[PDB]
Image: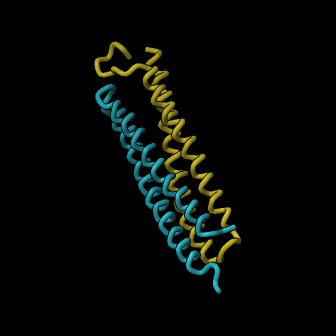
Chain colours: A cyan, B yellow
Amino acid sequence: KITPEELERIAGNFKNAAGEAQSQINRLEGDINSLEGQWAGATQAKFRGEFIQSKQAMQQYIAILEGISTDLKRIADKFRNTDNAY
Amino acid sequence: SNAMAEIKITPEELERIAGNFKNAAGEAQSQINRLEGDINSLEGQWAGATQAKFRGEFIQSKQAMQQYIAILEGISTDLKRIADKFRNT
């Protein structure tokens, strides 16, 4: 059943997912960075460029998840103020 | 591989990093699936206009994730191809 508590739980799932996603992109960025100076510059340019594209996608993703979490919490508060009318 | 001055990275190191990208792609797919299940669990349990708002935003996130996953898998594949290339020289 949808309750304010359930909406808040799902909001937490979205917020936690955004954090995991940011951590993941941070770890992978470190790997690409570590290759700098370890092979040809043109090869590094390719992987840095592709990584930056992945980073742009993840920036978009995180922003959307954070918005969903915020909006779910807003609706949960509305539910908490609508529920149990008497 | 070894002889060329600017090739310093070993094939095994490239394969290690490739594994990180492959694993990240898998984790990312599992994540978007869990979150989709969450939005799905709300279907029909609140107003259609409310569900429509969240479904639309979620689908935007889902497309961003699809793009990301595709890029990560390409990076993993390419790193392994280059590791093979260096291992042969």
Point 54% across, 46% down: residue? B28
Q: Is residue A84 above or below residue B76?
A: below
Q: In screen coordinates, is A85 left or right of B86?
A: right
Residue B88 spot, x, y in % from top left: 47, 15
Above or below: residue A41 compared with residue B33:
above
The count of marks equals 0
In the current view of this chain or complex, which residue is farthest to the front? A86
Q: Quadrant of residue A3?
A: bottom right
Looking at this view, is B52 or B80 the one in front?
A: B52
In the image, is A29 to the left or to the right of A77? left
In the picture, which quadrant includes the C terminus of chain A? bottom right
Which residue appears farthest toward the bottom when viewing the image? A86
Residue B79 coordinates in the image, percent (x, y): 46, 30
Viewer-proximal residue, A48 or A27?
A27
The relative height of residue A51 versus residue A12 in the rendered view (above or below) is above
Q: Is residue B4 left or right of residue A65?
A: left
Residue at screen point 49% across, 59% down: A65
B29 or B37: nearer the viewer: B37
Q: Which part of the image, by quadrant, shows the N terminus of chain A?
A: bottom right
Q: Residue at the location (39% across, 37% down)? A: A47
- Indicate the position of residue A56 as horizontal and vertical percent values: 40, 52
| Image x and y of residue B67, in percent | 51, 51
